[PDB]
Image (cartoon, coloured by chain):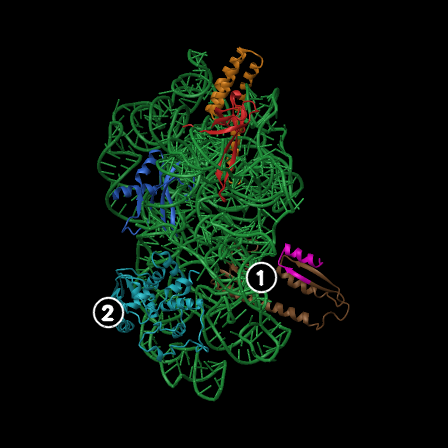
Amino acid sequence: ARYLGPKLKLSRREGTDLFLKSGVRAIDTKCKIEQAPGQHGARKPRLSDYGVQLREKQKVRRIYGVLERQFRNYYKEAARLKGNTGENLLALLEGRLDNVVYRMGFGATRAEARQLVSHKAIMVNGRVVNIASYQVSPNDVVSIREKAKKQSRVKAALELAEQREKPTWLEVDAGKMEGTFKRKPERSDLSADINEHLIVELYSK
Amino acid sequence: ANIKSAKKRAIQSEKARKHNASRRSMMRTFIKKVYAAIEAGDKAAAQKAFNEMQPIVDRQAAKGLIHKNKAARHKANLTAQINKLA
Amino acid sequence: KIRTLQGRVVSDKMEKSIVVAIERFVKHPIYGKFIKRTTKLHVHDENNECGIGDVVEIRECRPLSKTKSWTLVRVVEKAV
Amino acid sequence: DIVLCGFEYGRVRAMRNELGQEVLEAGPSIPVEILGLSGVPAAGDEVTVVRDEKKAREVALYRQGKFREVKLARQQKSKLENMFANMTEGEVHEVNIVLKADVQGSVEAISDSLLKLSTDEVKVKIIGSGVGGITETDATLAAASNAI
Amino acid sequence: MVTIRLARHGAKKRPFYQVVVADSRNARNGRFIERVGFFNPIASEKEEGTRLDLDRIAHWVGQGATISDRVAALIKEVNKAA
RNA sequence: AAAUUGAAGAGUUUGAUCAUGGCUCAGAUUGAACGCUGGCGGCAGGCCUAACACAUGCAAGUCGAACGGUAACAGGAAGAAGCUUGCUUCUUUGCUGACGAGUGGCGGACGGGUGAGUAAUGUCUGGGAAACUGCCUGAUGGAGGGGGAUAACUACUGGAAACGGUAGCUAAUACCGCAUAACGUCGCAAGACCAAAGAGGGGGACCUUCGGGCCUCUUGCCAUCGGAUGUGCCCAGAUGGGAUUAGCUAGUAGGUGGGGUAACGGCUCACCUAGGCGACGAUCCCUAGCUGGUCUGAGAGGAUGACCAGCCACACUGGAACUGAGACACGGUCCAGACUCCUACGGGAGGCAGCAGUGGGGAAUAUUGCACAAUGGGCGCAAGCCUGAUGCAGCCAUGCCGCGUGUAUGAAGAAGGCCUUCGGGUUGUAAAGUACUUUCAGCGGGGAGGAAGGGAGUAAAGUUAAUACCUUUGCUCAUUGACGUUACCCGCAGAAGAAGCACCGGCUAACUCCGUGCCAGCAGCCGCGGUAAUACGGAGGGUGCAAGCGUUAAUCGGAAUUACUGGGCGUAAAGCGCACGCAGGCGGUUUGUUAAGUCAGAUGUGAAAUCCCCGGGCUCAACCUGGGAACUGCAUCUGAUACUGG
């Protein structure tokens, strides 16, 4: 139910950094970042219209750690919801607990944050939530529970976090290891070389 | 029958059947006497017979052997015809 | 409260009965054209006052025979 | 308790011992007829109970695969053994039989004795040995090729 | 006769009852005449959990409808609540 | 506030083209199966085939507060004794807590199963009038005085069994007279006529035949008029196909009268009239349970009727009625048929389309489980008993949803493999190493909720002669969970036990080498294979999915490819060889009228669930749930009169 294999392969295939490692290292010193995996990585894909749509959807999925079934269901919900579907898809992803745990800096990666969640190290409103896809709401307070507070992963995670751009819609107290999901992120909060409308196109045909 | 009470019910329903049959046969007899008088043209015999019949079609109604409406028609019908002749 | 039908007499042969035809236009469920439909009713005509071709007003009542559950209310137009 | 006999598996529905119609418990000494198995097992074999049936499903199907692989193996050899498109002589005339016995112990045992009466001149072979009774596909089996 | 009782809906281990007026012979979750309340035995009790149209319940009693042991309890409980 | 605010195209005829036209693909969906693989959980689903046949258990009982009663076990007792003098065992007696068999009452018409039959004594929508209706309910009165029986039992007797035969004998809320009898039935009226039953709980003077009287309350019984629920009946529209089926019909259509039903009715019979149906599809033939809804589609449609709910029909096959408020009875009766079982040979017995289970058929569909704790049904004043309804558990990846199978760091980037122009590229931060976490599975510890009630006491009110009893409502005490090792929480051990499947020529995301050589083989469509095959088979690499993945089957979509919305017929499939013409469709222009079509409004109905919208509850989700909106439909009334019809 989770992708467990090599991670930089995914970045290499999509042509971009997917933040699947902590960021302690320039990614180009860990892999040949600008070349696809495999014997024929140097080869260029003269890539069809379907192809660009597929790869964009894969990219987003691989960023958030979501497999097809759940992600399709995410599209369905984005569509049902009011307002722009493409933007609704990203709101839903960005509201996941494993994700939010990552953005408050409690985990070096979404993979690490997910493990924190699954392993009962995260509370929401002082209540233990251990499922990664838990949808987090405005004004919620997610926190590292007392016993998980001395984990060195978390301190390192918060350090790296302090060096990333700081997300607007979250208020994080690094000392308490608690943080507040102030509001749903706008579209403008999220990276601009994500092409949701391509993903929207892939799932309407 | 297979079930204990099913057996008992068949026994009771047979008893009731022979009870009802007996009273029902009696009743129709007393109804038939009236129609027979009518068909012979006698007011008195037919009125007399109607008077014997009345209390028993009424009673068998009260006793559930027949419904009230049946008792009534019989009285209505015979009364109609006997009057129409004398 | 006098629910009623209007139609014309297609048969007056029977003793104290009549056959009445009620005709109406109906939208076709699929192709939209308006189609004629007819409903023939066996109706009671005590006194046999209804002639064939007459236009008559009828009403629904209890069963009067295996096929009669309608009786005559009154004649409207006659002997065209 | 789940019981596994040969390549057959299943849960026991009921237990019968000799004349006794029902027995609650059975010891290593006294024999008890077993019931509720998927199908009629081999005439004899080693039987072992298991904790769960799901774990014993793959094992039972595994034994079928081997028994089926050798079945097709012995089928290819006997046909190819002649190394010629036909028989070298006129013994080609043969008789076919169809057998279904109520008991599983007999069909394997008496067939061996039924192959003893076989001769070079006339060859007899058994087709579709049954576990019991008779059936539609069995009568159909005797319909295609003339047999008793 | 006509009775007022609980038809058990909800899910396995999470009972949820629909209070209904019905011919007592019909199945518990089958044909009913009128729905008249509900009863959640698993309500958090932080908010609601038991709602009865007492006006229609009484109307039906007035016409001889009987009442479950469990509905007879709910009614005394709800009458106490307010 | 919101609540249908939604719609894609690709390959393939040709040397190439445009058109025509079929085939094929991308999508959703499934009660699926098979092949490979397979960790946990929540919720759902699970004989689609043979309405084939079924061993065994269980699925309908209950009331001693209707009745005679004791045979079991349980005490109790004058009196027998265990006697070691208060502990007792048996002989006895229903004295009573109870209770086998019996009469009696209520239930066995519900609940549960199936879809064979049925194109209509069906269903859906909407209306009618001639009716009955147990239990529950409001109203008003009865509940008087008698009689003959009978099961049980006793004696004698026949049977292998099933089950009988004689004569005794006895009870009742069993059964029948008699009285009483109207706001009931018949009748214009005068009049005439119809019923019943007791049983318990407690008790003050009072007293006897010590049974009770009598006092009191509960409950059942009878009558009549209502309510509520259920059911029967009637009309209209709609609800499959076929003309290689065009005529059909004697109870047939109607009328009169008698009979009949709970009730209208050719329901039935006699007589009379000669009708009734049919091209707006009768008759005949084929097929089929209908609906809410389900799947698909932007929609209009198309397909469909498991699981949930409503109606119908059936209960081995054909027929029949008896009992009853209700049945022509799913575990009742009778006859006939098919079939099976028992037998001591003479005779008997049964009907899983209830729940498990078996054989058979099949590509294929589960345990002969636990519990009445909860909801609900039957009986009972109750306690309670019964409940394969139901709640649960087992089995299966069948589906949906959730989670895991680790996280981070880790380079000249090892070995091995693979490609290479031998420079190197790749597998690949992948592995090893380094720290780090412990969900789930394992193991110990603790521990919600589903529980409302019911039981003893107590107190107050209504009762009443009464503080009894009864009933209601408060109080305390001790109690009721099949699931269950529950949900959930804490602790321990270690990355430890948890990854496979299909694909990579174009459509279509993913390319190379070796082997083969029109072979072996692939193939949804085009089309691959005779020496460079990205198409066969293996490998390395890669793509897509992931506890699944593929293949097959199946509906709709794309298919504007049955075209109502939404197409065509000169040469592509398609104008009858030509004309006349009945039915039918359509019909110039003006006025008046009508108001069926059409339009408007109002009212009722359109079950709930489902779908959709906004909320609420399970850690999330599936799932459960509140309210709304929607059900685009039907019907009645009242209007409007331009258009269509008269």
Q: How many marks?
A: 2
Chain A visual colour = cyan
Q: Position of residue A148 (x, y in %)?
A: 28, 68
Relative to A96, does residue E29 appear above or below in the rendering? above
Chain displayed in orange: B
* Residue reaching furthest to the right: D90
In which quarter of the view is residue F440 placed?
bottom left
Chain letter of mark 2 equals A
Which chain does the brown colour mark?
D
In the figure, the red chain has which letter? C
Q: Amino acid at mark 1?
A: Pro
How far apart marks 1 and 2 lie (CA) works out to: 68 Å
Q: Which chain is green?
A: F
Considering the numbered disc 1 on the image, is that residue within a helix, a strand or a loop? loop
Q: Nearer the viewer, residue D61 or B72?
A: B72
Is residue E18 rendered magenta in the image? no
Residue B41 x/y as whole percent: 57, 12
The crowding category of the residue bearing disc 2, from other C-alpha atoms within 10 Å (few below 14, some 14 to 19, many at least 20), is some
Q: Which residue in the structure is indicated by mark 2?
A: A174
User: Disc 1 marks which residue?
Assistant: D41
Considering the numbered disc 2 on the image, is that residue within a helix, a strand or a loop? loop
User: In the drawing, does residue E2 fall left or right of residue D18?
Assistant: left
